[PDB]
Length: 265
Image 1 (cartoon, helix red, strand yellow):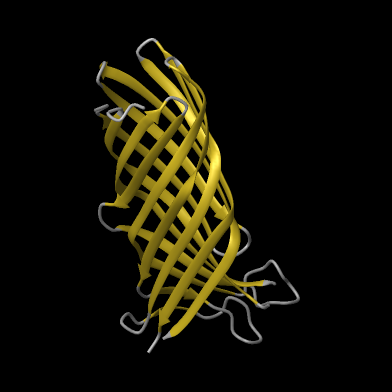
Image 2 (tube, helix red, strand yellow; image 1 turned 45 degrees about the horizontal axis):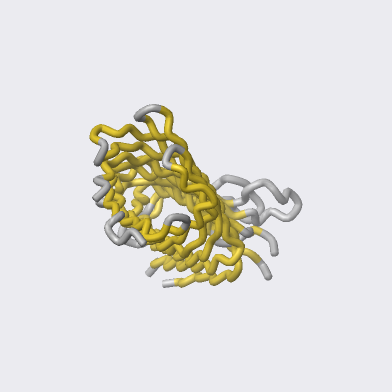
């Protein structure tokens, strides 16, 4: 029992990512709203506790610091004679990721807790939420007996789009850790095939609400960390995480490059 082996690490970083909202006929993609965001400022807090030699509990969380502009494109594969060719396309440059967040309670089973090298089977629950807003834009639509003829822009104030994504994912995985000299390399992998996903597209065109709720979807996350012990009681670290939620349905791909200070308390 080690009740004082606690930890605290506030981190700072960038989240770049993409969200795919697809409309189908119950299953054929007739529409795809591809939302995109790059280098959005985020902050990540975390607590950890090694109360047991081979067992560890922890709690992470990250939030966007403010909104970040992006881009959305709705394409519609209405032509049947030419399936993979898009029939109508809507460009939305005034897209903006309003917010993005995550919380993650986890428990790790240390197969090895040797001071220089640690390896643990991981298990826990994560809940990620994402929110976007678009406003007006360009259109490359196709008339009835034509193709890519109509080519204008929606008068602004007569069009607005709001998309949200909510993923509740219980997961399992593997946390690794190795220490050469004063440097600490390592990495992790997380998997869930029990993801409850939710989407909500509110297209306000003076409102149509399209929402999907898939259950038991998938989640894949690979993390890679590299740190250095400035003091024996503090470690500055950098970390890249690559995430993917899929199966298609409510899809999300994310890349979070973060860096922060872990004051081992």
